[PDB]
Amino acid sequence: EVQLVESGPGLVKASETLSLTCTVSGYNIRSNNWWSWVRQPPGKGLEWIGGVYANSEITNYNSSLKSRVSISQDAWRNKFSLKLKSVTDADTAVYYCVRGPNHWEYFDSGNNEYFEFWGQGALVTVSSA
Amino acid sequence: NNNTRKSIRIGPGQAFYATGDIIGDIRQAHCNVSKATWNETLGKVVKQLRKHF
Amino acid sequence: SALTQPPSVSGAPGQRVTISCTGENYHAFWYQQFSGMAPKLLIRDNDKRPSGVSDRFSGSKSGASASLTITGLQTDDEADYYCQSYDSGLRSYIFASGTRLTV
Ligand SMILES: *[C@@H]1O[C@H](CO)[C@@H](O[C@@H]2O[C@H](CO)[C@@H](O[C@@H]3O[C@H](CO[C@H]4O[C@H](CO)[C@@H](O)[C@H](O)[C@@H]4O)[C@@H](O)[C@H](O[C@H]4O[C@H](CO)[C@@H](O)[C@H](O)[C@@H]4O[C@H]4O[C@H](CO)[C@@H](O)[C@H](O)[C@@H]4O[C@H]4O[C@H](CO)[C@@H](O)[C@H](O)[C@@H]4O)[C@@H]3O)[C@H](O)[C@H]2NC(C)=O)[C@H](O)[C@H]1NC(C)=O
Ligand SMILES: *[C@@H]1O[C@H](CO)[C@@H](O[C@@H]2O[C@H](CO)[C@@H](O[C@@H]3O[C@H](CO)[C@@H](O)[C@H](O[C@H]4O[C@H](CO)[C@@H](O)[C@H](O)[C@@H]4O)[C@@H]3O)[C@H](O)[C@H]2NC(C)=O)[C@H](O)[C@H]1NC(C)=O
Ligand SMILES: *[C@@H]1O[C@H](CO)[C@@H](O)[C@H](O)[C@H]1NC(C)=O
Ligand SMILES: *[C@@H]1O[C@H](CO)[C@@H](O)[C@H](O)[C@H]1NC(C)=O
Image (tube, rainbow over all chains, first blue to last red):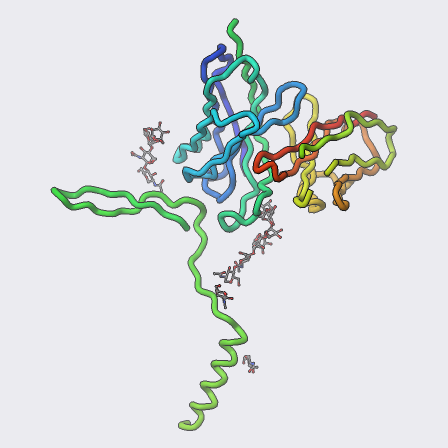
């Protein structure tokens, strides 16, 4: 029963880090599933970043762009907390946050973790002007 | 489950090793058993124990 | 390595059309996307159709490709469609670009 509401700065300027937090509602932030992000720049596909694995310190990233990000997971408030480092104007997109498949034992699905709950999506455009 | 240690301090030189967070979801703790084995083995107990009853 | 999809499709209503993907040894997942609306998972676990989606969708995996069929095309299905799957590029889900249904 997840309903992910997100809210970022609204308009970031170039070479300044932006941050978004996806408020989780109707569901705890401890269910053995991956808590991850994704972006959809107009045109190219649903480029993905990585997740946090509900409240551990364990992560995987998107080497397809690089290892800039350092996402955290602060619970007890149901925050989700992305952080993007060293942004240029090429990073503009619309950002979605999504959880995993809710495994039973910590890693049941070897490597599937398909993205099944896309909450709302939020967009931020990065520019010097 | 997969818990975490937190080190309270309760005096000069005394650390109390309390639990921190539970990482994951609360499944139960269990110990299975075979079932064809436990049925056979319980069937060897009755054959021997009939010798006294 | 990376996957690739036909850029576009077309077909009149009341039709049986399949959207096909390239290729691995893993499964594949299909996502729809309305214009201006957040994407939603539509087919997972090659067939294993989730709850709340139309029964008119049905996936299947071939020797090295997977395609999903749809019966009775309707205007509300003009959305894009994405082929999603992992690869052994060491990491990094390598789902291809989508194809938009045109009626
Ligand atoms: C001691 O003995 C006991 C038993 O005697 C041992 O415990 C057994 O352990 C088994 C494996 O560890 C376990 O099997 C699992 O059962 C799960 C139970 O599901 C519950 O919910 C469903 C509702 O959907 C009920 O119908 C069911 O009765 C249960 O109440 C299953 O959910 C598991 O199946 C999943 O994994 C298998 C294999 O991976 C898949 O074939 C299957 O389709 C399921 O796949 C889902 O989960 C994977 C995990 O990542 C996803 O990748 C996948 O996409 C699916 O996820 C979606 O679908 C599920 C719904 O199925 C949904 O919830 C999820 O959010 C996603 O949408 C698995 O089969 C036995 O149940 C368990 N027995 C008991 C009694 O607990 C114990 O291990 C023994 N001791 C030791 C030390 O070993
Ligand atoms: C049982 O209840 C207790 C409270 O009665 C609860 O303890 C709370 O734990 C959380 C998380 O451990 C604490 O939240 C902290 O809040 C402070 C101030 O808001 C932050 O500075 C902390 O964050 C730091 O660390 C994060 C990770 O590096 C950073 O993201 C962050 O920027 C900070 O560096 C943290 O969020 C909270 O303070 C306590 N409660 C009290 C009263 O102090 C506990 O979690 C409950 N049990 C369980 C199992 O949750
Ligand atoms: C117990 O666990 C061992 C671990 O390898 C496994 O080989 C064995 O089949 C298990 N037996 C039962 C009855 O659970
Ligand atoms: C298994 O247990 C049942 C329980 O009464 C018993 O009747 C049956 O004989 C057992 N099986 C064998 C092979 O002894």
